[PDB]
Length: 219
Ligand SMILES: [Cl-]
Ligand SMILES: [Cl-]
Ligand SMILES: [Cl-]
Ligand SMILES: [Cl-]
Ligand SMILES: [Cl-]
Ligand SMILES: [Cl-]
Ligand SMILES: [Cl-]
Ligand SMILES: [Zn+2]
Ligand SMILES: [Zn+2]
Image 1 (cartoon, protein in one colour):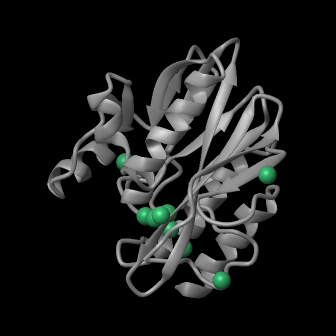
Image 2 (cartoon, protein in one colour; image 1 turned 30 degrees about the horizontal axis):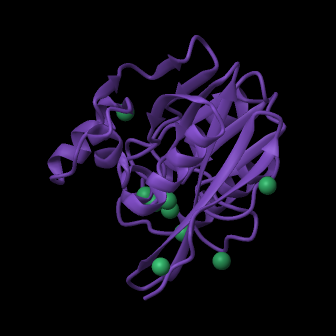
């Protein structure tokens, strides 16, 4: 039952990928991705690590390097996105999630984010971070995060890696809608140079085209 420690690796200027793990029944050890976004001495977390231990490590790294931590946002309700919300809340670090995500956390007896993002589109940190709802896919609540300054789309678990043979855990998925939702994201984010999936290797807009195709054949 050992798991690796969190690691933090640079994607490009001002953008860091955090990778953490959990052992999940039926899947074994699973790697999970989130980001730290830096701008003008401030930091913002996109999805928490998958444990308290790793959330603490990440926050310590941010503070060690002199950055002001403005908070976290989670891109859907499952534990690989939200495990550290309680830890962040208890340490007085602002946590954010959408109305739908916070509703689903409460329904499943989980600690909700302190702040709620309303509507299909939201803006964080004075335009640095844009949150967009493409439609149902992996879950009904899934959102993507666009970083206009970096030309990065963080897809979360709405986007699959290129080596993925399937859509992953589909127990709560909207498979028919997912292909259309993926097209919505493709049409909106033509500028995207880098796309980051919730699990697996980063790439370009090809990840969205592959995800779209996977959804089409899963139907
Ligand atoms: Cl361990
Ligand atoms: Cl990388
Ligand atoms: Cl997930
Ligand atoms: Cl929604
Ligand atoms: Cl997933
Ligand atoms: Cl695979
Ligand atoms: Cl997966
Ligand atoms: Zn999920
Ligand atoms: Zn996931």
